[PDB]
Image 1 (cartoon, rainbow over the protein chains, first blue to last red):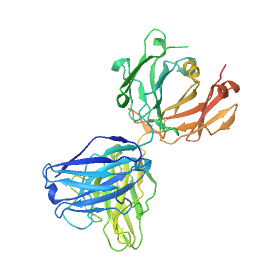
Image 2: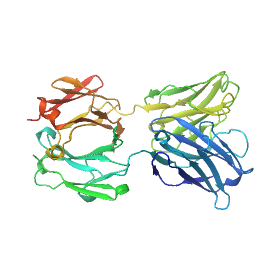
Image 3: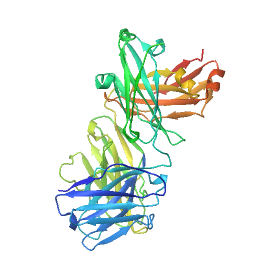
Length: 222
Length: 214
């Protein structure tokens, strides 16, 4: 009955603020009660506050005083949440959700797709890329694994393709570790035929849009 | 907020019946406030699953059912399907904090695939990384099921814990799991020892790989 569309992922320093939007399509958004709920990585659900646009009234949650500001633009049919004085613990996916029309605390029957918000004192950094070279150590029968190590970048995400997208079979790109230094790393492996080692060229293509850097690294045997 | 208590994990094979408990107190469940459930498929937003303790919104399968009793609520899935593998949260209202209270979350696993033993590949630091005055050991664990592994690292068969970073397992494009472990070292630490080992334990089995600076 309602389509909720949230704005894009956001990357911020401590102390700055972030505004997220939730655009409704269908139903009668200006009659509904709108909440914001956040989910920290690997954690549960946390209510930020609600707005009732019928009365122009906003009920923020006790944990966020002055920090949270909720907002509807009744013309463009768009809800907003602004969280200020960001800290790293504010890192979460933020959801727009509708409860029904009313002042009660109803269930959330409709939910936007979520907005990733990352708060970190880290600054944008492209990765260093190192070959994980194949050898007997990575060979077992008909298959050999080789890879690329994508080191110390910020922020997420990074994409890796092999031979410019030509090679997809046998490829796993792992999720990133987050280091104490605030920087990310991941690996990408491709399992290839053992006989192709040394006569087939393999190049990993790392693309880090947030830092505008692309890296092509050829990965060779011993 | 996360004040209703649920078990962290629930497991079943397809066709099995499972239940998830939602445990609250007198200021919520409790004070006769309704309980609702949300389903969160991996990578997606929560969707309403049960509302008003027991009602199903349109297009939620018959499998799912809810009840509440005294201070607890319960979600039942009678006939697990592969696609039921997700996180489930109960929610309600707490008059002692005057707001929404959520459950801690339950991960249900649908054991619908036979055990798969892990493939383990260990890479030593590249000389290129050494020229950069860094050194990183890379241990990649592939194609295992179910999705729990432990990784231990050793230098000369003696344990290390500092310098270790490990990703939680996640599915591959063949529905088995992969995971990775990294051991950070200085080039000097690296050149000291005789060998380094990555040790992977999965369902009572261990696979150990080794690399040497020589």
